[PDB]
Length: 107
Length: 107
Image (cartoon, rainbow over all chains, first blue to last red; front, side):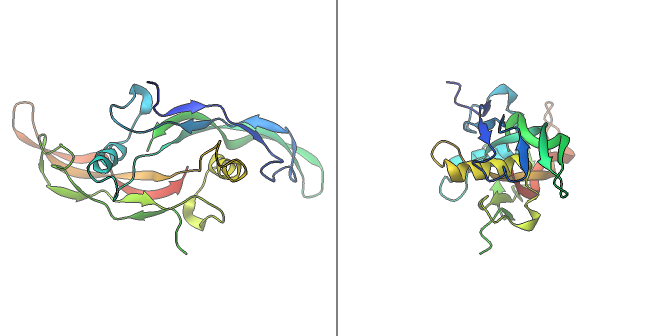
């Protein structure tokens, strides 16, 4: 129950991923993530493409030859970061795009 | 070598997936599929989002808690199908959208 593709929390520390060299702040942010399966019956809000549906059916028929559709971010949102200028000046990037999950779906 | 996210062939038979009831023709089509890993170093044309990069690094640090980015279709193309009208009349759907992979990427 409720095991399908959905947005869940993912707290990211920039030091952990080696970005603290060029990102002064914040130290961490909420990137979220997309988790869950793409299998029938699908959840209503998965917004699945026709190809994802086709591939899921093919995987059912031939599970060893063809993989499943994948639960992935389908829309992303920006965050603000404070980063080192090439001259060293800490500088605000106000909309640093593509950093946090707005919506998930099967693709 | 060349083990990264790319488009590969996938031949789909509509009877195999139970769509032959409402799809008269064609019998099969080339849907392709997206196969390969999302891991560093990335291929040039993966067009990875920032979130996919972040998640891949987090997965490296914490492989059991956080999954990898996923190789998925990022652009799809239509095909034509001949389908049964609700009145039974075979009818052409000229651009049946979202049926075949145009491009793959890590998301």
